[PDB]
Length: 98
Length: 9
Length: 274
Image 1 (cartoon, helix red, strand yellow):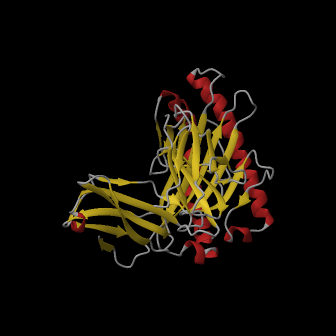
Image 2: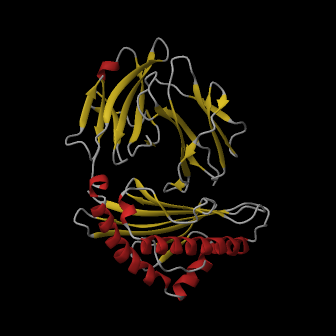
């Protein structure tokens, strides 16, 4: 029944400094649905953040897309904070262009 | 189109 | 290729913050077209695709009517199941329902679906004949007997192989340039040394539709399916999906490897040597 989320941080299009884009945090394969997800800019929580509608796979586990428009710069770092009942501690996955 | 008929469980 | 229409419903009880959170999503293939959320300000079945917006108000009124009826039975089902299982009102529980249908390239009925889950475990499901049910535990058997006695599958079958199928065809036509489109994967490979003796080869697929894709790593021809890491196919958020597969390889033997890519959007399967 209980399942740990799998977390992916990535951009919609290949990142290009100075060009607006979308930062995605995709969480899938988890259960139950109650889950906390934040997108971080240099550690600061981002407020204007959208998420998709709750849905599930053939095994009943859930998936969600959290996303926000952004403009990547060379120096700025982005990450995703996920908190879920299966994690002994909130997990922070850093956005890696590579 | 959603189904139009419903039955409790 | 074939098509499908899927509805997904989720109800989670909030003890004791109030009443269940209810969320409903409709899909046509890998494209969401409608949505309902009990917490949204709208309190209406909402469109999530351009082609569905064509439907008149009688359609929308009808759909929000039906989606609230759905939630009101899942709301009552939570109460009923808690009683079947002898559970306390303390804990929070989840009911999940999926139903839908597949049609072929000529729009002929293919398969009908309806499966229910409780707390992330199979509860009850309609078999492929669309005339009988399968219970997962002794609680679901109580439900099974009730539905059999009332012949509830008949009306359900009439929807799955009839109404569902005819409306799916309708959507596929109204949104033909969106739903009957195909977007091939844009592919490339990246190299990642781990140590002096090893490195990861990663095969990327980007911007493809629909979401079904097969990424295979090959060595001198053989398939390395046994030692490959795949991530779950992910939405780019613009209607297309992304995915990659990775092999850990002995350096320097990277040149013996090839990525094989299969996708409905590709005329011929891809073979990429590193």
